[PDB]
Picture (cartoon, helix red, strand yellow):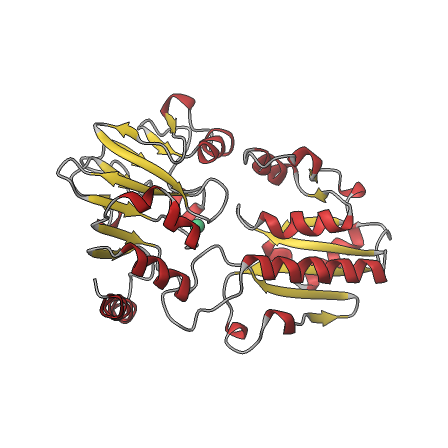
Length: 341
Ligand code: NI
């Protein structure tokens, strides 16, 4: 059964609630983004209205075969009426097509559901600036002060400089980047751009990328692995055994692998700066774990909430243990006392 924190009071709406069968009283199902923990349950046999971004709707149609007549794509930054309720979709700074949803309830209450997001000051100048929000349904993935990580720009600088150095020293080195879902495309696209290569990948992953409206993409990606020196592999194959096996398949074109695993946070964040990151190495194979996050750090989250000043916060992540819930509630109270709302 659907949990309370996926239901929008005063409406017929749910958010990211496709794995519960027919939800009692639900007239429209919203989907914030195309990640499996959120879309779990959708298929060609779904016959209720799904409301989402254009990019998310491309992925539903092409990857899950949802029928077109039930996909309702909405433009961003635009007031729309859904089953008699005004809604706005805003960029979530997560993966491609990911949104936050503003609901303007018939009684005057305004609710923001962040979906999954990486808070940024640029959000303080969207349509959020223009009215008060009463309730916030918050992505609390990294809601603890130990969670610090660098900007995306510093992480990409590190990756480009690392790859360009390695391949310029050894033109027979292959670069490999791990993936298991959409998101974090800048990692492999920025590396291919500095090297003058396309990114090579499976037909299934090329298909997924072609649903994303990324400009000039036919220019950056390919299924011809032989023409590419940046390859994308499943995240599970980014280990010494999996990479040795891949290098065998390349027929003596290459004699070294430099591989990247974009994780979110790992505890080596509490001690080491991005500048100081080193790989794990075995023979002619090196593997870099890089802290490329598409969720808010603790400080970015705190700043957003202290700017927004909601009356009530409903966490959507880490809600299954009493220790996590108590921790989060304690930080929400601190933020409110420090800022004065
Ligand atoms: Ni996500």
